[PDB]
Image (tube, rainbow over all chains, first blue to last red; front, side, top):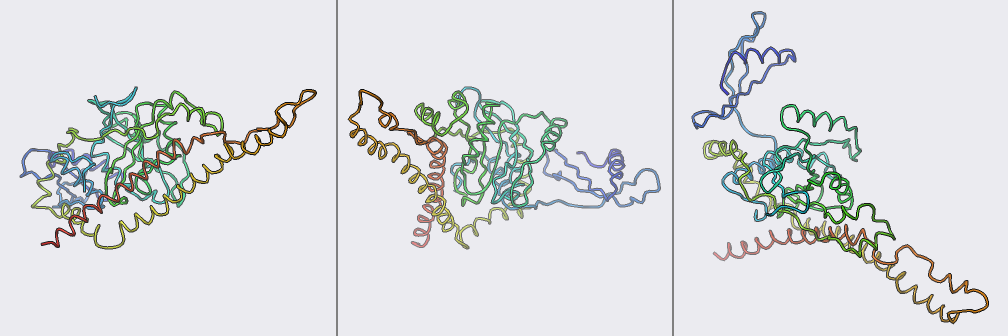
Length: 91
Length: 324
């Protein structure tokens, strides 16, 4: 965090040297539950023959998904965050 | 002080490590045991704390072949630049068939442990053992064998280091009981992703249902254990057979030949009398089974004790649930 800055415009340019479309993730770390954990963004306009790069970011939202046993792995850490939950008495 | 023997404390494996292990979960090394990464950590309160790992890949086409260390050197610099340093205090092979500490894993460990005595060797065991008990198996090597250092040769120092009788049912440290203090952020995600976005929580939890119903889990465990363990059992029996025959059954014949000589010829040798016992290779105590094989008796008792338990639970639940 925090959301859109002048540095969005700058880490645009550095990533535009790779030159596909960018995927700007901003992980706000604030206490509140009214603050989303990570706020995915991708610029529209983004026309680029102008200054450096226009910043008007599209609404995106986030999920989890790559694998099962690794979110069994995250659930194992969720309920360790609750309270350990060591590995002996699982079943 | 739960701390280990003579150079090291226990281990603590921070959750973000084990996330990165289950990313290279059980592929890139399924049917081949591949060292899937080094455990990089630091000495903390009464423990090590593995705070990060980076994976070590290899040429895994269908066999494993060791590669240039251009990977590890560049990647341990990659860690050093944004994070800490190259602080490899162990390693993890997940990998292949519920927790088993092979003779090769004992030898690779022996090279590792003698070099850096701040070490454990992890064996990350997911759903493959029917999950099951002891998902994180730690195990460091006895400092006795790091004092009767190399090598256990077939006749000398098999017998002699068997007679020293260093451990092979050796202690394994506990790994977690405490707040790791990087609980923090992942705690904050729990309230989000439970209730109002419990998609991916419930997805992970309902994995349990289909761990029971379908194709032959305990059946296949007990099947693979019907083959794995009978292999090892037969091996010790025919190993022990031949050696015990060189120990006694050959002494039996040659000493009954020593009868015939009458145990002395005064004018001249005693060539025959001398040339009785001329060494067969085991005189006693073939060591690599006695040590390293016996580490896997322990692991085979563990697999049996694991596969049993979830069976025991069903045998309560099944009867009881229907009893209403």
